[PDB]
Image (cartoon, rainbow, N blue to C red):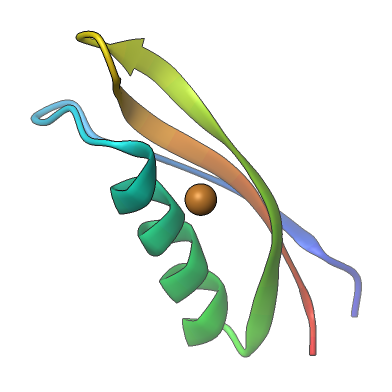
Length: 59
Ligand SMILES: [Cu+]
């Protein structure tokens, strides 16, 4: 297994870093992997974002 790069965004809500980190973490965990890195996408408002791109790696 290698690590997998994944991209998620929403067109209906802007959310904080914490929400997107949570989404990335839980996505990797559902795939039996661990989140290694991530970066926010599509900054919104003064402190929010509309997506995240992240890398899930083998346990
Ligand atoms: Cu974070």
